[PDB]
Image (tube, rainbow over all chains, first blue to last red; front, top):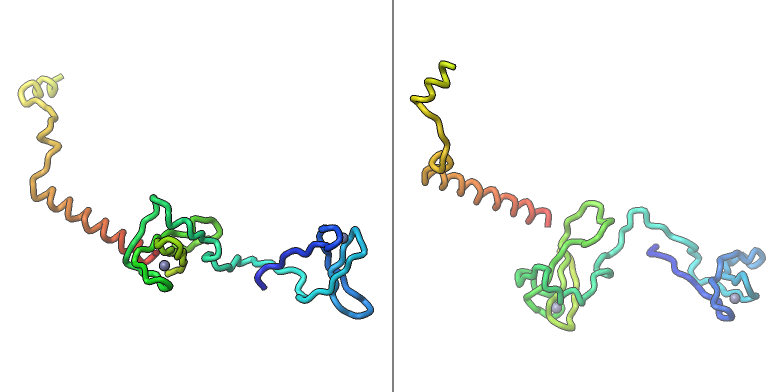
Length: 117
Length: 48
Ligand SMILES: [Zn+2]
Ligand SMILES: [Zn+2]
């Protein structure tokens, strides 16, 4: 699933809306303010993640290695570059709902590698 | 009336001496806290 984004009209940059081509039996995305229509590649119209399962490592920002106030450890070396010091922190978020997982970020500048243990 | 007049002989007070323990009591108190903190760290280490 993931999530489903938006398509915009080439003529007028309004949002394209899904509708069926009832005679070819194919999903179209179609503009509501002009004649523009686009054939869909995806078939999926919509997904909704009640469990909110997503990889939080996509939401950790590598620049956070610069924060003076986070704890850092050589006890967990980075895979990509081998650098010993990593900064570590919890979710810093709602919607973890329970967990106390630690996320690690490499402190070596311009490495920015992020992982969880 | 009679027992307040007896306290005039026995007296009552409180001071710094009453608030102090012996050295071995302090060592037992400190060793309890030292372990208790380490136990919390082990809970944190499992949670993390
Ligand atoms: Zn349009
Ligand atoms: Zn690294």
